[PDB]
Length: 267
Ligand SMILES: O=C(O)CCCCCOc1ccccc1CN(C(=O)c1ccc(-c2ccccc2)cc1)C1CC1
Ligand SMILES: CCCCCCCO[C@@H]1O[C@H](CO)[C@@H](O)[C@H](O)[C@H]1O
Ligand SMILES: CCCCCCCO[C@@H]1O[C@H](CO)[C@@H](O)[C@H](O)[C@H]1O
Image 1: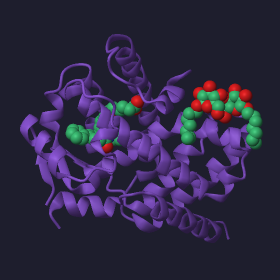
Image 2: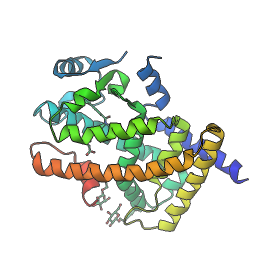
Image 3: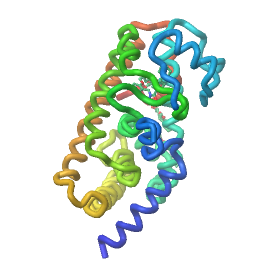
Image 4: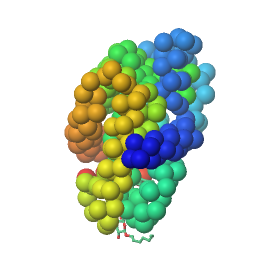
């Protein structure tokens, strides 16, 4: 009965995921393996791509131009905000989330979206770079390394996490549950109805446990491995937030999007 009810639960969350995210891991890995994106690996190809690739965010809508490293940061920032939007619609497509009072919904999103973003980011990452512009471009890890501090520093740790997370070989059906577990997290500060969020979280984690038994029958220790990845993401986001505070302090000409400011306001 428990195993049965949780199967239906997991399907409803997978459907919310397919409905709301712009790219699946299945799509992204098929592009990344060739089963072609324009490669951005230096200033000239960055320029050609801004001339020749279709970006969700028209380049004129980015903040005013400053320099190459900041331009790259602005595109990272636009994508981050776009993914907050998708995560919000994903969360709202989950009935037990939509039943929480709107203020707790905000609290969960505030402290959860970056963790979820960096987990999902892995889907479009390999050891050599990552997909951009809805898969029509590929930016190399080496080029991102070449940007000036503090912008190269805030990027490289995400690759390190991603290459390790991708070795677990989750598919989209696993990720939908994993992400749901990250957002529906009863530990976040200032939650109003904690026992309710704890109850939902535990349901998701039991559903995820059974899902991996069925979907990855020969993978050992995969559930506890993923719990530890949830702990790892928390530390990745702590470090991210600290790097953002230094960018705010030392790079005063760099615009920071007000929604992300609201997230960092008191972490
Ligand atoms: O959190 C904030 O306050 C926003 C600030 C985040 C800053 C750190 O963003 C990073 C870091 C590591 C890996 C990926 C991202 C950003 N990102 C992206 O999808 C992304 C988008 C565009 C590019 C790009 C690079 C060169 C040329 C053209 C485009 C690269 C990456 C994932 C959403 C998270
Ligand atoms: C059900 C809709 C009506 C909700 C009204 C309650 C709003 O409370 C506010 O929730 C915010 C988190 O979202 C906190 O940042 C604020 O400190 C808090 O004051
Ligand atoms: C769009 C979903 C993600 C939203 C993330 C941003 C949340 O910001 C918070 O909004 C609250 C009022 O709602 C304020 O009380 C807090 O001061 C502020 O930190």
